[PDB]
Image 1 (tube, rainbow, N blue to C red):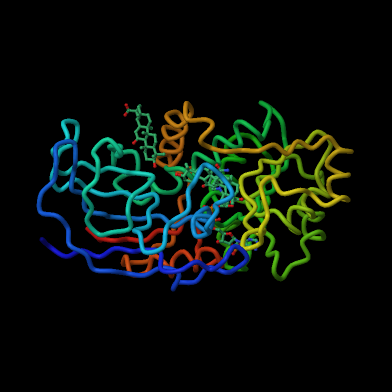
Image 2 (cartoon, rainbow, N blue to C red; image 1 turned 90 degrees about the vertical axis):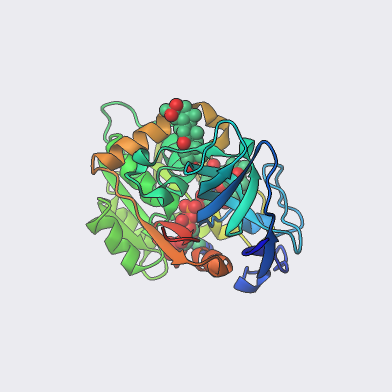
Length: 349
Ligand SMILES: NC(=O)c1ccc[n+]([C@@H]2O[C@H](COP(=O)([O-])OP(=O)(O)OC[C@H]3O[C@@H](n4cnc5c(N)ncnc54)[C@H](OP(=O)(O)O)[C@@H]3O)[C@@H](O)[C@H]2O)c1
Ligand SMILES: CC1(C)[C@@H](O)CC[C@]2(C)[C@H]3C(=O)C=C4[C@@H]5C[C@@](C)(C(=O)O)CC[C@]5(C)CC[C@@]4(C)[C@]3(C)CC[C@@H]12
Ligand SMILES: CC1(C)[C@@H](O)CC[C@]2(C)[C@H]3C(=O)C=C4[C@@H]5C[C@@](C)(C(=O)O)CC[C@]5(C)CC[C@@]4(C)[C@]3(C)CC[C@@H]12
């Protein structure tokens, strides 16, 4: 047996705690030399870290959609790899495959049925895009806008995006323009990200919530109010945005990342004053869970791919190398170190 590396849950930060690199631990383990019928041996190429993983660090995730990781057991999440050996009828050495529950380990023996083969032509050979813009975050943005945004044919709406330089947000803002908004404004956490948005991703304006006057800048950059809010963050930021939203406007309630490490359920309740405004102005604020639109994954991926290949959709990512950096990458992402999709490259081939 050859020795490979893997990552296990070392400790929990507590439901009110901050995640740190050291909640995870690297181990060296043997990889079995033989696989069974129906199984494949895969080499891991890229792994995703994503905010929802914070929940799997707790004893109770707070939702049936994801289960808690267990102390000292291998952790898992979105991944992409290449088949090294197959005893599954529909997979063959050299196929590129993805799983939602890829164990954080350099080489893995997996049930062939748990994997999906992917076509690298969809991403011009940039396989890591399958974990981001031409993956679940991209679908979340495209489907969320389609289903919850109500961007009418021929209209000239203003869209605001929170978490605007992250995975979902950076795509959402571009899609807002693609699909007919005349104004797209992003809110994000650094001046570097503001520049990215307006100089590369085509946002009409960007606001740094840590340093700028958010209400003031939204009044300046959204002179006709806000019709569509793609909300990744919640909290104080969303209160400020909602206060400037128009009658019959729409909140795409993607995530509420500002309410993490507090024991706060989703959808989190708007404060009394902000709920009053929401209701007065008939602002819609429904649950949105991308998995409820599985039937749109095919056209969604096909559209994301097309826009990318056309040079319209600009795909940003921040890649860190080495499985030993999974914990660091997750912590970094949670605290805003990522521009676009946070990726960890496990083998650079
Ligand atoms: N509804 C769905 O089906 C669905 C699907 C996928 C993801 N999501 C959710 O959508 C959200 C975005 O996920 P993502 O994958 O696109 O992550 P991401 O935006 O790429 O990364 C998270 C970012 O959140 C920002 N942030 C962190 N703490 C914050 C705070 N307290 N206040 C404001 N901003 C903060 C940081 O950027 P700054 O530098 O700008 O602070 C960080 O880079 C998360 O809530 C995620 O769980 C929902
Ligand atoms: C996991 C995510 C979100 C992504 O991270 C990687 C790509 C992918 C795994 C993706 C894929 O790779 C191939 C197909 C196929 C494309 C197509 C056109 C075909 O090739 O027949 C039609 C059938 C089929 C199954 C539709 C569904 C998708 C788009 C499928 C599985 C949706 C889920 C998707
Ligand atoms: C496909 C699976 C099963 C998983 O394989 C990948 C992540 C994910 C796509 C996952 C996600 O990515 C982000 C969230 C959010 C996390 C959280 C805490 C927030 O961020 O506000 C609360 C709101 C919200 C939408 C709850 C639902 C989940 C857990 C959501 C969509 C459930 C479905 C889930």
